[PDB]
Image (cartoon, rainbow, N blue to C red):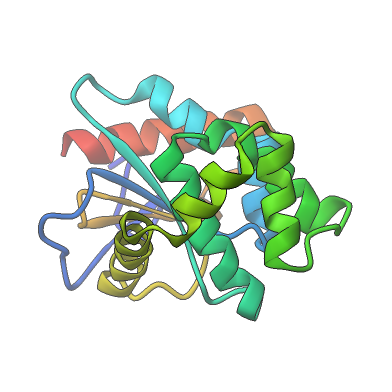
Length: 188
């Protein structure tokens, strides 16, 4: 066939019921995630090709970067609660990996302050129980699907994208193959 289990995707031997339709995992410590977001814009191009009616969830993971990794997952919870993903994603990636100016929670906070979220808004969200449940969700979803590596994308709790089985000679072509696969998986 043209799309084959084990080729552009893999199937979970233990399917995850009630999972978000298109589910993406990342970490601001993850070098390929940096590529996926700032060079390739994967999440964005996947969207562009998803059918109507399908929502995409993106979650941060704990297993990279120790203490700051967990901080970063809570701040991503804050980002989601406040709806400011599109304003902090890039400065967080560049803070962790480019300039290396993120070394503590406080530095994570500075990014939000600079992106225009108010101190009192940030701190309240940071400490809110809404954010604690939203942290819990991020952790649960990672747990449900065995998650040991990022970037990772799961469709309908049953399929897992396998980008290593796609040509990388051309970056535009890789993205579109990626996006088309998610589309195919979605329709399955």
